Image (cartoon, rainbow, N blue to C red):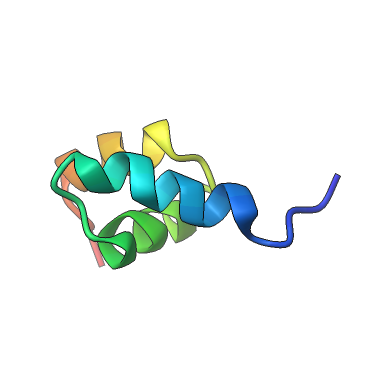
Length: 49
């Protein structure tokens, strides 16, 4: 099922509270495949590009 974006911004907001602006995590989503948890584990490893 497709995702308009809801969960997306919800990833941001969660990982957000975790000291991760919507952009770092969403971009992390672009780098996480849309996943949030991975989005932050990404926030960690450090955005390669």
